[PDB]
Amino acid sequence: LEYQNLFTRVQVRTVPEPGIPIDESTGTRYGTGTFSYLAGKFGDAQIGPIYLGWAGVLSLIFGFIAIEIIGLNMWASVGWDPVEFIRQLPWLALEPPPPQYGLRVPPLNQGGWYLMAGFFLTVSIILWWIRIYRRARALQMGSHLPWAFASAIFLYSTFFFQPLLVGSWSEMVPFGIFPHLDWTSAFSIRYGNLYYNPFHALSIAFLYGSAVLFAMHGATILAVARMGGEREIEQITDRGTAAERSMLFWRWCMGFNATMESIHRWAWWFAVLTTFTGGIGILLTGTVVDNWYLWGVKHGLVAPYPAQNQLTPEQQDLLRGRYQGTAPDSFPSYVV
Amino acid sequence: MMEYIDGAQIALYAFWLFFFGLIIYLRREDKREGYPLESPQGPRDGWPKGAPKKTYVHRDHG
Amino acid sequence: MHRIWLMYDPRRVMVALVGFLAVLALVIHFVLLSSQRYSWIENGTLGADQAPVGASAPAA
Amino acid sequence: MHRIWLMYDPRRVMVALVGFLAVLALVIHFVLLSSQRYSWIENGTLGADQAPVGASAPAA
Amino acid sequence: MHRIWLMYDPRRVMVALVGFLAVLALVIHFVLLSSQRYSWIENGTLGADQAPVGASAPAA
Amino acid sequence: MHRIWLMYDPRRVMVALVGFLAVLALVIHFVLLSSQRYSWIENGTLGADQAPVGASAPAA
Amino acid sequence: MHRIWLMYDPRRVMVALVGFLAVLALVIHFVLLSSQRYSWIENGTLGADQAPVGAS
Amino acid sequence: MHRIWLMYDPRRVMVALVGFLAVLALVIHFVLLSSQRYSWIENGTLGADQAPVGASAPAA
Amino acid sequence: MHRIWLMYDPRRVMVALVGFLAVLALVIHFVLLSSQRYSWIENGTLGADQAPVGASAPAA
Amino acid sequence: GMTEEEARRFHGYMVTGTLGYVVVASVAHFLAWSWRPWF
Amino acid sequence: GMTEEEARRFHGYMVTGTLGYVVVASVAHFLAWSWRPWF
Amino acid sequence: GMTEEEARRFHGYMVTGTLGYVVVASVAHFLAWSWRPWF
Amino acid sequence: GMTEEEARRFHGYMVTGTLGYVVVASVAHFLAWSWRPWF
Amino acid sequence: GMTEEEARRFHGYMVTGTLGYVVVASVAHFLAWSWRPWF
Amino acid sequence: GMTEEEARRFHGYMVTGTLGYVVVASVAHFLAWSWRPWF
Amino acid sequence: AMLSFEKKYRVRGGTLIGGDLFDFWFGPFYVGFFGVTTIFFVTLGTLLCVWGAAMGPTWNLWQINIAPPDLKYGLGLAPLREGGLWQIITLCALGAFGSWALRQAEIARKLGMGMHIPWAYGGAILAYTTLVVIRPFLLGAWGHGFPYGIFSHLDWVSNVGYQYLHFHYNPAHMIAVTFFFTNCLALAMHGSLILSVTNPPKGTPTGTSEQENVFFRDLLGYSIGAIGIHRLGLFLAVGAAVWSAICIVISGPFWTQGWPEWWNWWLNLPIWK
Amino acid sequence: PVDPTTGQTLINGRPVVGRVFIMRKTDGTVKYPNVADVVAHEALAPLPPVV
Ligand SMILES: CCCCCCCCCCCCCC(=O)OC[C@H](COP(=O)(O)OCC(O)COP(=O)(O)OC[C@@H](COC(=O)CCCCCCCCCCCCC)OC(=O)CCCCCCCCCCCCC)OC(=O)CCCCCCCCCCCCC
Ligand code: BCL
Ligand SMILES: CC[C@H]1c2cc3[nH]c4c(c3C)C(=O)[C@H](C(=O)OC)c4c3nc(cc4[nH]c(cc(n2)[C@@H]1C)c(C(C)=O)c4C)[C@@H](C)[C@@H]3CCC(=O)OC/C=C(\C)CCC[C@H](C)CCC[C@H](C)CCCC(C)C
Ligand SMILES: CC[C@H]1c2cc3[nH]c4c(c3C)C(=O)[C@H](C(=O)OC)c4c3nc(cc4[nH]c(cc(n2)[C@@H]1C)c(C(C)=O)c4C)[C@@H](C)[C@@H]3CCC(=O)OC/C=C(\C)CCC[C@H](C)CCC[C@H](C)CCCC(C)C
Ligand SMILES: *[C@H]1O[C@H](CO)[C@@H](O[C@@H]2O[C@@H](C)[C@H](O)[C@@H](O)[C@H]2O)[C@H](O)[C@@H]1O[C@H]1O[C@H](C(=O)O)[C@@H](O[C@H]2O[C@H](CO)[C@@H](O)[C@H](O)[C@H]2NC(C)=O)[C@H](OC(C)=O)[C@H]1OC(C)=O
Ligand SMILES: COC(C)(C)C/C=C/C(C)=C/C=C/C(C=O)=C/C=C/C(C)=C/C=C/C=C(C)/C=C/C=C(\C)CC/C=C(C)/C=C/C=C(\C)C(=O)O
Ligand SMILES: COC(C)(C)C/C=C/C(C)=C/C=C/C(C=O)=C/C=C/C(C)=C/C=C/C=C(C)/C=C/C=C(\C)CC/C=C(C)/C=C/C=C(\C)C(=O)O
Ligand SMILES: COC(C)(C)C/C=C/C(C)=C/C=C/C(C=O)=C/C=C/C(C)=C/C=C/C=C(C)/C=C/C=C(\C)CC/C=C(C)/C=C/C=C(\C)C(=O)O
Ligand SMILES: COC(C)(C)C/C=C/C(C)=C/C=C/C(C=O)=C/C=C/C(C)=C/C=C/C=C(C)/C=C/C=C(\C)CC/C=C(C)/C=C/C=C(\C)C(=O)O
Ligand SMILES: COC(C)(C)C/C=C/C(C)=C/C=C/C(C=O)=C/C=C/C(C)=C/C=C/C=C(C)/C=C/C=C(\C)CC/C=C(C)/C=C/C=C(\C)C(=O)O
Ligand SMILES: COC(C)(C)C/C=C/C(C)=C/C=C/C(C)=C/C=C/C(C)=C/C=C\C=C(C)\C=C\C=C(C)\C=C\C=C(C)\C=C\CC(C)(C)OC
Ligand SMILES: CCCCCCCCCCCCO[C@@H]1O[C@H](CO)[C@@H](O[C@H]2O[C@H](CO)[C@@H](O)[C@H](O)[C@H]2O)[C@H](O)[C@H]1O
Ligand SMILES: [Fe+3]
């Protein structure tokens, strides 16, 4: 019943909408500001003009062609049927090359479009990084954001380098909603349960810690927003009672605290380390360790359970299978 | 030819040394406000000792 | 040489040094203890010619 | 060497030293207690000739 | 020797000491209680000649 | 020895004491109830000649 | 002996005490209720010589 | 006796009481309904000698 | 050349240099320790004629 | 808060409330016992 | 803050209530012991 | 804050409460021993 | 903080109590050793 | 901070405590050695 | 911050302590080599 | 010890239970009645975890495994060495987490803060309570809870997922994952922005809310604003835990088949059946 | 061994008052020593692919 600061009953509007302050060359602001009533009820109201420059324009051209290649291959895979393109959409994929090609260029239908879409997507992501970096400099800001984004790009690039290091493009992630989840599950199966990869475990701890911190910090700032705690830059340069009370809450709760500035460093590192430890864990997989559960047995991670079955010595020879080979390329008659 | 030592383990201790270094750095940053602590036995710094309080240059006029 | 201690505070360097030597010593001891040849807590009483040795080059 | 106590507050150094020694002692005891040869809570009453020894290099 | 209590508030040392001794004692009891030889709740009535002993090194 | 009550607030030493004893009592009862020899709720009516005794394997 | 109520306001003790005893009584009943010998909801009619004994 | 209602707000104690009794009544009915002997919605029409009973101790 | 110390603070450079050298040395040592040829803790005593060598044959 | 006479009259209802509740429960237990006794 | 005669008055009730509870609990154990002894 | 007089008074109850508790505990242990010795 | 006279007085209790605790523990090890020696 | 005479005084205890500790550890190692040598 | 004469006094302790440490470590390698040479 | 500004805040009052009785600090920590109950349950639960390690096969931290009972025990307490200990530790956990949230409410009331932090933590408690209370209750046996062990509980997560053949296809799980990933992205942007205006390149003036607002608006096309980003971060982080609770409670109690075949309703919409 | 006189277990030749059971850790679980030991309880390694 006490006002919760979750919703704003009274917005105000300025007849002019703010523009961009400085450094308009090699690129210019597109559009002009407008106000959204819904966005203005969640948060701030101005849907703005936007900046691209050279890097942003090129990023969109490369990224459009990548997405266009993905979609057209998906749509071709249901025979151009537009009803099936929508009905089956999350099952559709643009799929990596066949394994026996290794790193060679594959046929166009058999993964040649995949590598082309993957190349343009990668260039598009790098140009978008350059855009963000240039824009941070032009606004006279620190480069904290482009290095945060570089950590995500690092994990993304391991989905290129680990297939390269194991020596086959067939090991790459298919472009598709459910297909890339099929790949994600099968990758953990092939490499013997990724739960025992310790860099995967670290990445999870930082993924969970990022949710812990944004829950704690989000709730903390809303609990003092009645005192201007959300004006964080002002609280950092001119500590008010809102900053003092949020420091004391955590000190009295758990025995130590951050500051209004340094809480944002904790946030930054927990997010960044999620994808950085993740990338390392991928790059070790199939290159250094091929069965993570057995690595866990070696290093003492695996809890012992009582045996569910016991094999006789002849069953140990009978129940070994074969490694999976090639599919049969003929349709046998059994007539004789 | 080391049987027990392997690259995944080597990487993991490399990370632990960085991470414990990082926690120290963050706990130094966390003490730029409110420290040194008041105590009936005089000032206290905790550990690590905090980084000094920053002074912020305001935008000259606008 | 001594002017290094004007560029750096000896209070910081000495704690950095102690921390470095602590970590380095523990790394070398635990690497050795994990080896076969120098797992001295299990095999320290073996004489030098009885202690494990890694396998030679293959011979055929 | 007593002027090390003018570089560093002895009240802080002693807490750090007590902390260091406690952690180190517990580490070494737990290393030994994990071993075979020095699993003394189970095999402490064995004679020195009877205690486990880790395997030697095999003879040619 | 008593000037140690000018340096440290005895009111804080006694808290630290009681905390340390409490955890240490619980550690040692649970370690022993997890052992085979000193699992005294199940086996405490056995004579010392009857109590478990860990494996010897085999002679050859 | 009564100076303890000058160093520490008796209102909350006594809360700490009652808390500590309650935790300790519950731990010991749950430990004994986990055992075989002292699962009194199910085997409490057995005489000492019937009561379980733990031993190691006969090691023939 | 009465001076503990000058240290502890009795109205604030008695609410705490009731909670502790309510939980303790519930815990003890459930420990018994799912033991073999004292699962009285299902074997309460047996009589003392027929009731289970945890021998093994 | 009535000075209990001078110590505590009667309104609060009535809400506390009714909440406890409602939850307690629900728990006991669920425990009975979840049992074999008292699963009355399915077996309530059985006579007192045909309602389930939990097994006795063995004869030896 | 010394203008390098005017462009960059030597205090900042020295940390970067020592950091680079320490990492590079640790990388090279563990790469050699992971090899067969140079796994010196296990096989350092072998002597150069019987130290491992990587496979020759391009063919035949 | 409340006056000691107002406390006095409230207590009489709380007592007779508790008594009427116990009475119904006691009859309910005797009915349950007559249908399927538990000892 | 409570006066010493108020504390003394409460203490008499608090002792008597505790001991009455313990007496009732002892009778409950006597019935439980008679029905199914645990030693 | 309590005086050394009050501290001495309080300590007397604390000692006799401890002793009374230790006595009850020791009787409980001797009952437990005679029922089922642990050594 | 404390006077040096107060430091001397506390040190007397602290050393005495520490050694008393070590004496009780040394007897506990005498008994434990007699029952089941660990070397 | 300390005055240098206090630093001089404290060091003498610190050295003696370090010596006393190393001595006890030296006996502990020679007991351990004669029980079960590690070389 | 230090005067140059303080830096010079510190430097000689720091050098001596480093060389002292390296001397002790040299004996440790002499002992380790005598027990089990790594080449 | 106290922060240099702290002392004037250390007033009495704001408790929910106990009043002045426990209204004091111990070092940095506020105690209170729920502090006392916190320490009780934490201590009892932790020592019973150590007891679980002692009677199990190893002291190796990664391998300790205090497992729930067999399903045959249903909703009863099992024998303590057969999973009843896991049940007692679970009660301590519920008591400790509940005491922690109520102690947070007492601290917030003492500082004149809104109740946002206790309720945000309630999201995590809801997920834990779903895993060990609600879902096992709906399945009719406490043995459906996860074991207490650093890696053995990951074995439980693996096996529960494959009980539904392909757990990625669980629709609430897809939403929960999307919240977790979106939260981590949003946290990196919020951290970066505040740091980059407060720590600009050397010789640049300190930034402003306007610069932060302009840059953010080039990233997403719209201004979120200062309170908006903290609302978003709270919505994302707590929504992730709530959708996690949903995704696990529907798995078993409500859906029993493989998760891929749940999507059959989408394939059979009448416009394209 | 059991004493024929009294039906009573003898440990190291001397009697035990009680009902002797062999102590084991929870459910008889035993820590995995090695990868080799884990692999020794498994089937042999799979045969090579048919390509
Ligand atoms: C998994 C990936 C993600 C995992 C993510 C994990 C993130 C964890 C981040 C938080 C960890 C630090 C917590 C903290 O700072 O608490 C304050 C306390 C004291 O310093 P202060 O606050 O500045 O000053 C107050 C004090 O000086 C005087 O206060 P007062 O007189 O009122 O009270 C008495 C004293 C007594 O001191 C203590 O009791 C300290 C005991 C600390 C033990 C726990 C250390 C955990 C380290 C974890 C990092 C790592 C260790 C290896 O002060 C207090 O009572 C303070 C009570 C603080 C209670 C904090 C409890 C935190 C438990 C965290 C457990 C985390 C488990 C994961 O700090 C410390 O004692 C030292 C902590 C130093 C930072 C850790 C750096 C470790 C680097 C590696 C070892 C370095 C060796 C040289
Ligand atoms: C059966 C399934 C396996 C499994 C298999 C894997 C695999 C395989 C991987 C992970 C990875 C991760 N897993 Mg796992 N995982 C399992 C179980 C779990 C559980 C759980 C509760 O059980 C959790 C919480 C997690 C959690 C996590 C994360 C910590 C981690 C991903 C970090 C990240 O931010 O990625 C999300 C962030 C990114 C992908 C970065 C992307 C950034 C780029 C720049 C974005 C480009 C967008 C572009 C511009 C536009 C695209 C347009 C379209 C192409 C049309 N896993 C089990 C054991 N998991 C990853 C990892 O790091 O492993 C070590 C990984 O690769
Ligand atoms: C720290 C780790 C976390 C993280 C961080 C992170 N990601 C980031 C950032 C950061 C800090 C950015 O700054 C960056 C960003 O821009 O954020 C808004 C980004 C980003 N994170 C993204 C996604 C993303 N992040 C993810 C994850 C995470 N990101 C981690 C959890 C995931 C997951 C979980 O899978 C995804 C999918 C993007 C939204 C964004 C990078 C955008 C980008 O690179 O876009 C390149 C451009 C294209 C793909 C092309 C789009 C084309 C359109 C169809 C328009 C076509 C118009 C026209 C036809 C062509 C042009 C014509 C010309 C004539 C004009
Ligand atoms: C709801 C969104 C996310 C969230 C938010 C969140 N967590 C929070 C908060 C908030 C808002 C707090 O205010 C609170 C806090 O104070 O943080 C510092 C907290 C907190 N989140 C924590 C952890 C945590 N949060 C997690 C998750 C999440 N927290 C969600 C994703 C996880 C995960 C996913 O694994 C963990 C481990 C704590 C640091 C803290 C709550 C501290 C607390 O309750 O303290 C009292 C209890 C103890 C100190 C110990 C209790 C010990 C038990 C009695 C015995 C052990 C039993 C246990 C079940 C064993 C488990 C073994 C495992 C190996 C399985
Ligand atoms: C058609 O041919 C393909 C390709 O050989 C067969 O698939 C093989 O077997 C599968 C196990 C595997 O998945 C696949 O990679 C591939 O190895 C497929 O089963 C059909 O087989 C029949 O025809 C085979 C063929 O290739 O002609 C024939 O194989 C035999 O004959 C050829 C030619 O004379 C000879 O080169 C092969 O070595 C020989 N193989 C064997 C194993 O004897 C199959 O005959 C037999 C006995 O296998 C055909 O199979 C049947 C049942 O008719
Ligand atoms: C599975 O088996 C397990 C479960 C495990 C086994 C364990 C079981 C356990 C441990 C059980 C515990 C039971 C228990 C305690 O411990 C039980 C305690 C029960 C009690 C105390 C019940 C009290 C009931 C009282 C009632 C209904 C009152 C009714 C009427 C009222 C109030 C008056 C209405 C009129 C008003 C208000 C107006 C007055 C005038 C006014 C205001 C005016 O005039 O001003
Ligand atoms: C599975 O097996 C495991 C569980 C593991 C085995 C182990 C179990 C363990 C360890 C158990 C420990 C138990 C324990 C330990 O101490 C239990 C302790 C129990 C205790 C202390 C109970 C005390 C009860 C006290 C009562 C009921 C008092 C009532 C008072 C009343 C009614 C009057 C109040 C005053 C009034 C109304 C004033 C009116 C006048 C006024 C105001 C005026 O006149 O002004
Ligand atoms: C099985 O495995 C594991 C568990 C691992 C094995 C190991 C276990 C271990 C290590 C156990 C350690 C146990 C231990 C160690 O020390 C145990 C030590 C216990 C102790 C010290 C108990 C002391 C109890 C004292 C009591 C009850 C006193 C009560 C006082 C009362 C009632 C009086 C109240 C009235 C007053 C004051 C008067 C007010 C007047 C006023 C105000 C006035 O006049 O003003
Ligand atoms: C995998 O490897 C594995 C297996 C782990 C193996 C490898 C292990 C390794 C690498 C070990 C390294 C060990 C090491 C390295 O340096 C260890 C170094 C240890 C050291 C330095 C110990 C020093 C101890 C000193 C003590 C105890 C001093 C006590 C002093 C006292 C009591 C007096 C205090 C003062 C008083 C009372 C006076 C007050 C007066 C005042 C105030 C006044 O007058 O004002
Ligand atoms: C597994 O195998 C892998 C790991 C793979 C193999 C590879 C390993 C590698 C790469 C190793 C690299 C090692 C290395 C590289 O640099 C190692 C370098 C080590 C170094 C530099 C050691 C230096 C030690 C210096 C010491 C101890 C100094 C002590 C000084 C003292 C005591 C005096 C203090 C001052 C005082 C007392 C003055 C007070 C008075 C004052 C102030 C007054 O009076 O004012
Ligand atoms: C008409 O227009 C239409 C209607 C078709 C437009 C609509 C399009 C639609 C509907 C598109 C739908 C797209 C969807 C649903 C896409 C889903 C994508 C997902 C979920 C992808 C998930 C993961 C993908 C990953 C991780 C891919 C990673 C690939 C990498 C890193 C590839 C790198 C490749 C390189 C660098 C290639 C280099 C080229 C070589 C090797 C040859 O030379 C250097
Ligand atoms: C096995 C151990 C081998 C030796 C270990 C190393 C420590 C040796 C200490 C005893 C030998 C003398 O060591 C010597 O001490 C003197 C003071 O006493 C130090 O001298 C230091 O303080 C004096 C003033 O007091 C300054 O003038 C001098 O410039 C400064 O270095 C020397 O730097 C150190 O070299
Ligand atoms: Fe913020």
Image (tube, coloured by chain):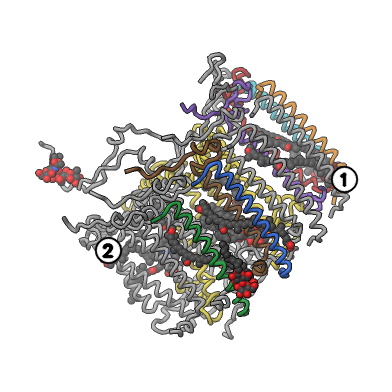
Chain colours: D brown, F purple, G red, J cyan, K orange, N blue, O green, P yellow
Q: Residue at x 71, y 66 (%)?
A: N8
The residue closer to the viewer here, D14 or A330, is D14
Q: Which residue is mark 2?
A: A115
Choose mark 1 or mark 2, whichever is in front.
Answer: 2
Foreground residue among P224 and A134: A134
Q: Secondary structure at mark 2?
A: helix
Q: Residue furthest top?
A: Q5
Chain holding disc 1: K
Q: Tell me where residue A188 appears, x and y as whole percent.
A: 37, 50
Q: Indicate whether G48 appears above or below D48.
A: above
Write the residue at 48% across / 33% down.
Q28
Cβ(mark 1) to ligand 7 < 8 Å? yes
Say whether residue Q15 is visible: yes
At 23% across and 47% down in the image, what residue appears? A325
Percent position of residue P176, x then y: 46, 54
> Which residue position holds label 1?
K6
Q: Quadrant of residue A54?
A: bottom left
Under 8 Å from ligand 11: the CB of mark 2? Answer: yes
Cβ atoms at labels 1 and 2 below 8 Å apart = no
- Look at label 2 and name its amino acid: Leu
Q: Secondary structure at mark 1?
A: helix
In percent of the image, x 60 and y 64: which residue is there? Answer: B48
Counting other residues with Cα less than 10 Å from the Cα at mark 2, is it few (<14), some (14-19), or many (20 or more)? many
Instruction: Identify the image quadrant of residue G50.
Output: top right
Find the distance from the CA under tag 1 to the CA under tag 2: 87 Å
